[PDB]
Image: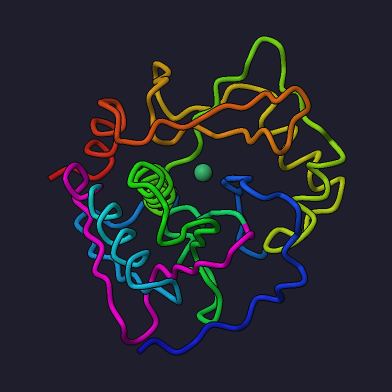
Amino acid sequence: GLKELRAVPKADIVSGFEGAKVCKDVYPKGSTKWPNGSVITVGLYGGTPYVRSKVKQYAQEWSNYANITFNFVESGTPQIRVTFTQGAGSYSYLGTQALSIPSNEETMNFGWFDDSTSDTEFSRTVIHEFGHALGMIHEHQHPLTNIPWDKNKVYAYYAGYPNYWSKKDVDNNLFATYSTTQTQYSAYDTQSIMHYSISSALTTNGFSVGNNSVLSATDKQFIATVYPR
Ligand SMILES: [Zn+2]
């Protein structure tokens, strides 16, 4: 199979955020569009056969609309390298930033899948992370109220693997970024698979915001414009 990746220190994975389904922005230590028509190699590291089959299943949905294909392989150094490290959050580098990640590290992680995971949850989270793998950013419609973060909790969550974000890192990279609307679309698309989920595990009111679980009309149109036939 694939050569194993360097080990995650499971002590750096922060405990006590059970059922926190957070997409983490991640940045390489230091254009993201793939060449059009690319066939991108993907390797899966760990996970059960069931979980790995679901990832394949939903990732490849993007190719219905984009002129990009994912070739799931078990040899060499795949271009996208997917782990299943529990509790680390889910994430992907953006687009061709994957190609900047050392070969012994992952480029994508799914932090909460198991063999009881719903089809909708696989669809939502897999398509979403693969959206970032194609270069899409979060859609975030900033609410009029502002977000009621439990700042203590937010600091604790983002302090560990993979970000290792200090308090100032969190204030600049998280609160600042998500204090205003963020979009890649002309009109906002409440339906986008790329919407940024705000977990109630990180807020104070029980406030949460969720993700749509399938590709929107706008998602389908945008990605075909980026990667046309
Ligand atoms: Zn995301």
User: In which quadrant will I find the N terminus?
Assistant: bottom left
Count of labels shown? Answer: 0
Q: Is residue 16 magenta?
A: no
Is 201 displayed left or right of 170 in the figure?
left
Identify the residue at the far top of this view. 144
Magenta includes 72? yes
* 29 on left or right of 97: right
Taking depth in this image into account, of 20 and 131 the one nearest to the observer is: 20
Which residue does the image show at 67% across and 50% down from the upper left?
A: 18
Residue under the point 53% across and 82% down: 5
Residue 73 image point, x, y percent? 28, 77
Residue 216 appears at what percent x and percent y?
Answer: 29, 29
Q: Report x, y in % for residue 13.
A: 72, 64
The quadrant of the rendering that contains the C terminus is top left
Residue extending furthest toward the left: 229
Q: Pinpoint residue 197: horizontal percent, then vertical percent.
A: 56, 34
Is the image coloured rainbow, by chain, by secondary structure, or in one colour? rainbow
Asked if residue 93 lies left or right of residue 206, the reply is left
Residue bounds of the magenta highlight: 62-88
Residue at 22% over, 38% down:
224
